[PDB]
Image (cartoon, rainbow, N blue to C red; front, side, top):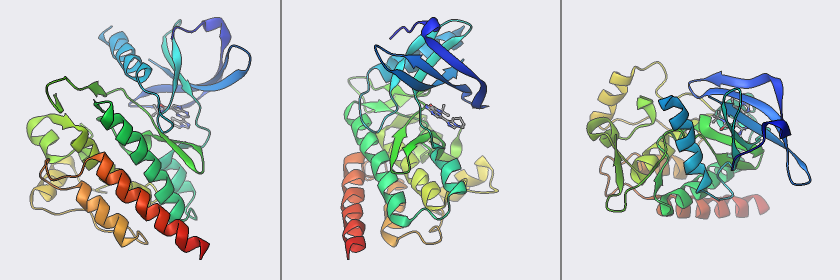
Length: 266
Ligand SMILES: CC(C)(C)NC(=O)c1c[nH]c2ncc(-c3ncn4c3CCCC4)nc12
């Protein structure tokens, strides 16, 4: 887990900065090969980076960004695998010709990652299109575990804002569970089928909460299959018990993906 600064070469231009800090590109000399990496650069703040690292250390799934390790040098640094096509929201804004079936394939992969996170009893707590990275046009991985928590053995929720991705019960009761990650996944789907548009455009946090309270929901993106819209809406079920878990969401996605795959072969 602890990497050697002298084996890491960082590009001086950064890939980006914002809420999440700074991300730089570099490469890291492995046992034999050299690996292109993305590096997130950072007192209770030292602890938050370590705590994110502690989470990622515990995860191993094809649809989750892999942590190479951490290094204390100029700054604390979290070194991750590189996703060349970058964040999914920025990619779809730039690539409007991306077909319906491809978008289904990408959000299915996200659901596979999340089903695994749910099984591991971690809550992500920041699931959004901006945190899905594209390794290829056909391979998405979840990242940014900065808010992620391991669930206690006795409860299915963590008790504590990107209000636009949050389920009512996060807003009402500060309660975060795999079910509220499913709410968040609905909005991520809405983002994906809207080619990376931000949700609830032009609305304030308070107005979104008010809209949700009256049972109103975002409408169907232009050209989004009804089956996918119906699934987003199921994700945004008010009642936490009746809202589907990721197993159910992943199965629904998988089966629809096979459907469209079969139609394309015809
Ligand atoms: C914290 C955040 C943003 C979730 N990123 C990561 O966790 C990353 C892990 N591997 C990556 N590879 C590329 C980028 C990338 N490529 C282009 N950009 C980025 C991230 C910064 C904006 C532009 N971001 C990450």
